[PDB]
Amino acid sequence: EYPAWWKEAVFYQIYPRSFKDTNDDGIGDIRGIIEKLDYLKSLGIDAIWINPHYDSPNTDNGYDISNYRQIMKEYGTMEDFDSLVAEMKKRNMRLMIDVVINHTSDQHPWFIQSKSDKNNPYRDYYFWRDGKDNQPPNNYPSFFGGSAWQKDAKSGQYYLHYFARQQPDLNWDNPKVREDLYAMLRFWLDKGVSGMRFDTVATYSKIPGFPNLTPEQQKNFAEQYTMGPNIHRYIQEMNRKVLSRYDVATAGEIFGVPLDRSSQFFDRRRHELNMAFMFDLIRLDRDSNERWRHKSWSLSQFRQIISKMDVTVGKYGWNTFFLDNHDNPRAVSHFGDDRPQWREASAKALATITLTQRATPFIYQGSELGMTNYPFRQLNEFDDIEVKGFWQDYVQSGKVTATEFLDNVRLTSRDNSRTPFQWNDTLNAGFTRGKPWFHINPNYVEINAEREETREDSVLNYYKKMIQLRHHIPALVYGAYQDLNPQDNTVYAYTRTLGNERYLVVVNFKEYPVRYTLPANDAIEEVVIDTQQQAAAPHSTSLSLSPWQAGVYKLR
Image 1 (spheres, rainbow, N blue to C red):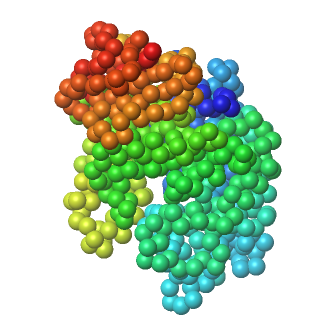
Image 2 (image 1 turned 180 degrees about the vertical axis):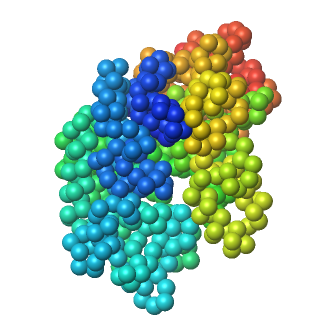
Image 3 (image 1 turned 30 degrees about the horizontal axis):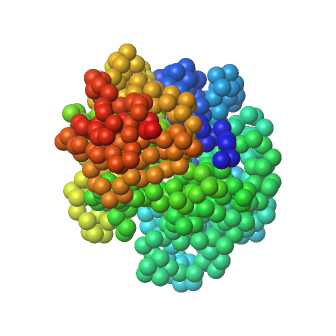
């Protein structure tokens, strides 16, 4: 069974820039988070993961770090940070920070020096290569558009950046970089942080010789970058050196790692990472070649990916469960139906699922309210550099029309989840009194924390109840997972079994009523909860489900 606090906990993710502004400069800050801790405690949150909070030019809103030990000016001071840990600790909440060490900002002291000369001490802190000819070293693509190699006029060589140009990759091969990184980690751990979320941990190790990519590898380049020969070597070292020497829950974002390779990252026995963030589910409807394009998916596909994950996780690993985050579109829009008539119901349905999985649930800020995608009027309303990067590679190239491109990024852009949190119905949704740094969704007049707090049938209060059920029913945390019908495209039904305590979770994914027949030997003994306010106790053999109806039941 191997109990663990991080396995039973309910995590909340905060994107500071968009959580709460306290000085009215239009940007969310750390004091804003402090101000809302009571809101999150009442919600039932156990731990909080905050996106990057370090000094950064903000080319990638925090993921381009220029100083790992300094608090981002936009977010506040060290005192504010220390105060967050203290206030959180006071409320028995654990703080998990975002660790971005696959790369740094091109304005980081290490890169500034590395960039000054070919013989500078820090030259080997990054990857510099010569373009054998009148072009880059190889054909490596960048997640943010064009080549993953940037030419340095001065020296004449190219430096490597999987992501933005302003995000040069660190060289983990050099034992000096590793040590400076471990020192930096203990800096934060010594201050009380109880958890670390490692950004793109599968790409720390590069492929020796930087061979070119075959036509095939060109497509799934995201996966090739995880093919590093020293990845588990390095992560294991970081564990020995740091992780294993503090009580810290670790989560690794393994973007690009095939499912059959995730085990090596979270297998207890391997002493690497406690749990991981897989993307097989959240990206089930993304085209293979065009990462920005959305394609149709079905429930059978959805549930089948979940079964596979559970099997792969097995008895020795552990997983997280999330339907959205700062790099993806809103959960209700993506997996439910955000139209006015179905938003609440489908939101509650997804909530039911989110808190009854054999994984640690991560609730992204604002989705507990049923926040939705943003109504982007035109291309320039996106800040997403991934989008601007896609525009260059597919629209400038003529590979896709601007209209079709827009139709799609409207559904897949990470900016959908980056609009300011909606607290109440005052100007700017009570987020700020200044000008919001990024456009706020007009539906805030309907979807806002305050309004939902007083309404018993609100999405917020339903989330409160689901989290409360998870905190009180062990089976919902550790019970075995069983998909009663992997092929059904209408009703998602599964059991959670811990000994003789069996629970049944049912979700009507359709917008018309459906009658669900329980397995012949199964009987409903109790109703733990359901999305209908009225709906009385059903009988033992079947359920008449209304559109998007969800429920948890205890079986005999």
